[PDB]
Image (cartoon, rainbow, N blue to C red):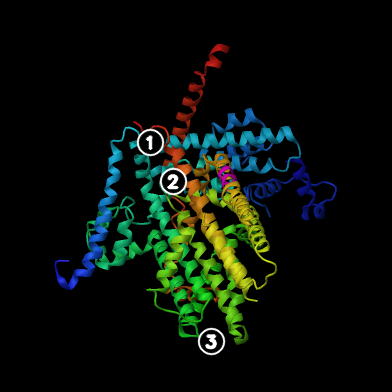
Amino acid sequence: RLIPATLYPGRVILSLDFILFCLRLMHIFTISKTLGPKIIIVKRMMKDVFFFLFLLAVWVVSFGVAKQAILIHNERRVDWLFRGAVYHSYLTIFGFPEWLTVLLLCLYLLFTNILLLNLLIAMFNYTFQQVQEHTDQ
Amino acid sequence: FHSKLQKVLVEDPERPACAPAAPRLQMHHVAQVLRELLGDFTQPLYPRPRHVTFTMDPIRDLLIWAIVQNRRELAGIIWAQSQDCIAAALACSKILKELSKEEEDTDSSEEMLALAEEYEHRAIGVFTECYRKDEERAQKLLTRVSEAWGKTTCLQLALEAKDMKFVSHGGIQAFLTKVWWGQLSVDNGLWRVTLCMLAFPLLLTGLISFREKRLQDVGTPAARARAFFTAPVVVFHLNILSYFAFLCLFAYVLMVDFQPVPSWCECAIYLWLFSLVCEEMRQLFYDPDECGLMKKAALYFSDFWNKLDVGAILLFVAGLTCRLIPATLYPGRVILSLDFILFCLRLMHIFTISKTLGPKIIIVKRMMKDVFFFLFLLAVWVVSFGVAKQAILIHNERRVDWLFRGAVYHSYLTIFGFPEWLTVLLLCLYLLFTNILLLNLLIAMFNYTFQQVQEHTDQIWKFQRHDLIEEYHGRPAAPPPFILLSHLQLFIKRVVRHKQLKNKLEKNEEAALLSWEIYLKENYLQNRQFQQKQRPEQKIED
């Protein structure tokens, strides 16, 4: 920001820095009589959920680009196309050619809200049962 | 055993050629049936012909003839005096597990099987000791070439007879890993691999580690980087990148460079896909033993993961020619798109070797079979719901290309996680079934199946870990870019093992080794029977 030729990127950077700080607040619940243990657990979990996050990412992005490819001949401009597509992906991630359309939609929804859901379901339950007892120490 | 022997006796051609009245039970027949029982990879334990004389290690011969007849006490006695106990115990485990399949009697089969696993406990028992004393020599033991048991090795017999408890001993896992890192150190983390892989001078720098500092301290960076490249861990990471790039590039060229004539890049990845599947097939014939071709075929046909890959191949060879015909260009686009996504799936494979997740994938691999079935039901569920909507809110409609499209999209939004009274009733019932019934259902489904397997899989994973290591240690060091020169360097010999997993030893060396083991086996024996003296039930009997 100090360099005026770098003012707008200064804005976006310092925004990031803000959010980073806001994270550090979970620290409250460290001393939490009643939750500290939990944070301990997720602290053990941070390492793997990161790795898994990667996969779901490439997952949806492959899906979206498949969409763009099948519904068009040629496109560009990821600043509105990929922006609106990533936003629609955020909505989907909050939780007679028509036959081709139905097939695409069904397969996509098959993978997105199912495979990875049950996956993490198992992941948490398993790792949970790995440590659920003695951390309080 | 006796029945089988009679058969193979009269099955002999040369004996009824000699005298059809006196079939001379000839020793090597026994060898033959044994080779069948033991495996195709060993040798015939007794030679074929064409003052007394023992053979090498008579005691083993006694040991077999006692085993096949399921004589527990006799066996236990003799084995205590065997020569190289580890291999012995294993071979016995293998035979017994084999013979316990085709016995057609219950009580005897059960008794057999139990005996078998009892021996693998013996094997573990000796080895855990011999390792607890020394490590390096203990490793040297897992991979010698037992001339007695048909020139095979202990580790093989382990894998053949499926001795999870053995291979998962943990000292073994230490050994495997020690190969995983190939030449260099085994404690350097893994980020250092990635970074130093990027920049060459990082290798010439002091950021990475090495074992046997005679090459670490004394630095000949040329062969140093060479040795580094030999480390299959790396060769793995090369493959993982090349794969990454191939995939996304393929996405690019289909996106923009899509051209009816074969674009420079389209033909490029065509050659690439061929290169990849070429190495794939290459891993079918390295079989050093006379491995059955239809057998390994049924194996790959059994590998669900191999099943995925081959499905994707069929997709390609289909869609390629589809696009190739210009009258089938647009459907060529949609097909090859599918093929893309299929490939992108195969990437979860990363987490197979995942120190920290592989087990999980194992689980979901067990789950794939049922979630599929359930997916069906939710599908028809929502679709019934949507069509009920369309029916109740209209008199007549058509055109599923916008109607069913927008309806299926609204269904995707719903699946991401005074007539008005009729409207409220419809909405309430629908939401009742959709986000509730099936949710709690799968909730139970996962929790139940989870509790069905949540404990011991780690074994299975530890077991699997091997063959992967075997492969990437075996494959020649050439990622798919420079893999074609390797493929042709292969086909030149196609037209005209390693010392890592199998190595003869020297009489002077081997002898000292065997004596060393003999000693420790005796030690193990004492501790066993002694701790037997403490079992309270036994004390009361006293």
The quarter of the displayed image where residue B184 is located = bottom left
- The label shown at residue B173 is 2
Check residue A8 for magenta coloring: no
Instruction: Classify 10 Å Cα crowding around label 3: few (below 14), some (14-19), many (20 and above).
Output: few
The secondary structure type at the circle numbered 1 is helix
Q: CA distance from mark 2 to mark 1?
A: 17 Å
Q: Which residue is mark 3?
A: B260
Which residue range is magenta in the image?
A: B439-444
Q: Amino acid at mark 3?
A: Pro
Q: Amino acid at mark 2?
A: Gln
Instruction: Check the residue under mark 2 and report the chain it is in.
Output: B
* Mark 1 neighbour class, 10 Å CA radius: few under 14, some 14 to 19, many 20 or more: few
Residue B320 visible from this viewpoint = no
Q: Quadrant of the C terminus of chain B?
A: top right
Q: Which residue is mark 1?
A: B133
At label 1, the amino acid type is: Lys
Q: Nearer the viewer, residue B303 or B13?
A: B303
Q: Secondary structure at mark 2?
A: helix
Question: Comparing marks 2 and 3, which lies closer to the viewer?
Answer: 3
Q: Is residue B505 visible?
A: yes
